[PDB]
Length: 52
Length: 52
RNA sequence: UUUUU
RNA sequence: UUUUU
Image (cartoon, rainbow over all chains, first blue to last red):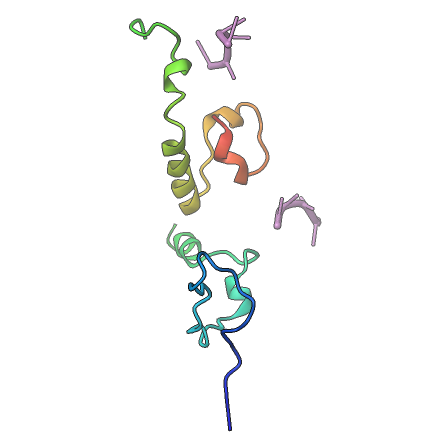
């Protein structure tokens, strides 16, 4: 006996009724936390400084 | 200029969002600010959006 | 979010 | 409504 975390009967928004929006294939998405923030800048900027 | 019945602003009031997205892009690359605030001393680099 | 000499 | 170089 085993199972998964995410579910489908959960209370979730619905454009229309049958649709479930937060598609439950997102099991694999956990990049670095700080890497996503705004407090750190972007890779492009980091490049253009390094080139200028 | 001599060939519009109301003024020049009253015709160019259309072209709003095009240059808006323009400055969004080319500011996202680099720290652009326009002229009109630099004479009037804006402070925030973010608020280039409406220094028209 | 900025503002720490 | 106009008047912002």
